[PDB]
Structure formats: structure tokens, C-alpha cells
Image 1 (cartoon, rainbow, N blue to C red):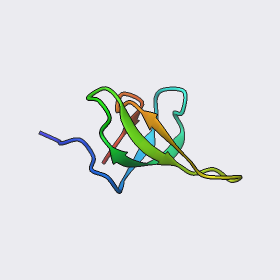
Image 2: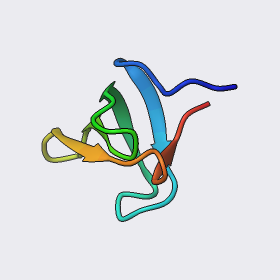
Image 3: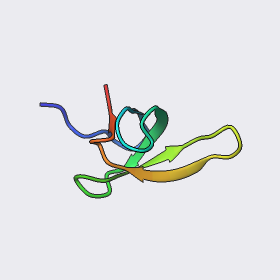
Image 4: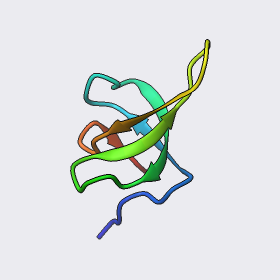
Length: 57
């Protein structure tokens, strides 16, 4: 029985449009949605993704 990731948790996006990108878990916005901080080479930008798109280990 695994529990959803907590704020400050690292998650790797594998499925979805942002699949293949790293994101930091922040707050579980919705059971099918979630808010994570995405960093880029130009600037960092927080975005929301669904666990079905990213997984946590």
C-alpha cells in the first residue's frame, strides 16, 4: 500500500505531455491531479500534473 507523494517529494514524469521531465511534488491538487515545481534551463515554472503522468519511488 503506497501513499501519494508529500510536498518536497521528487517525482519523475514518464507518461503525459510532460513525460520525460523532472518535477518536485508540492500539494496533491485532486486525486487525479497534483501540483509540482518544474525547472527548465531558461527559467523555473510550477505546473500541475496527474500521478498517471508521473510516478514516485
